[PDB]
Image 1: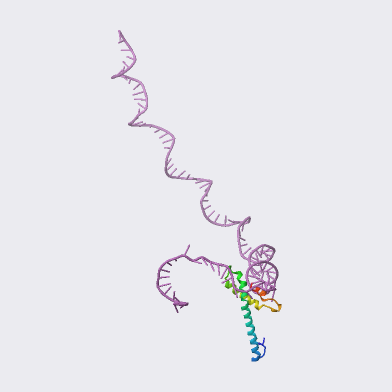
Image 2 (image 1 turned 90 degrees about the vertical axis):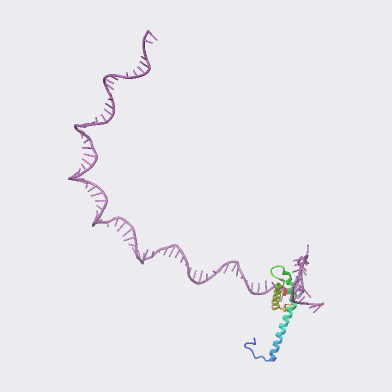
Amino acid sequence: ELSERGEKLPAAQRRDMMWICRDGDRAKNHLLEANLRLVVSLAKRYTGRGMAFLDLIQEGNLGLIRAVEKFDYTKGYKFSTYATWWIR
DNA sequence: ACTCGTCGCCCAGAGTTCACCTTGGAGCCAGGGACGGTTCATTTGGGGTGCCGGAAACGGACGCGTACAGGCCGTATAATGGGAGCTGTCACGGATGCA
């Protein structure tokens, strides 16, 4: 929003924004790497027809990325229950 | 004691060839119609036509609805590292990981 029709952000006011953005991206990556195990556990069930195990795994990672993007913690629900639908 | 089978013989004839009159014709030419292949006048019953009036089918154009086909999107107790594959060959020149 500030990029166009904003203000010239000083170093003090911009470094905080950059740091919190990087922290958020790092947290997203951490959650992805944590839930990859659920991804592979879910994807183990569709082998033997059509595609390969690695292809199924990568599709599971894509679904996990989508679920992480569309997750909502305010509902007070465990992440696996929501992510299973997207992975499937 | 004797003839009817068979021999020549003698005359009528007959149809045959020679060599004679007649007389129905083959053409042969002349002459004279009527007739039809031909030509030339009509003759107006009929073929023809161009054309748009124009009525109407018709073949397509055009604008606007409808239908499945394929595509995108989402489902909130929990669900967190995998099946498997069958391997009795022989030689061998050489790279290559560990000697």
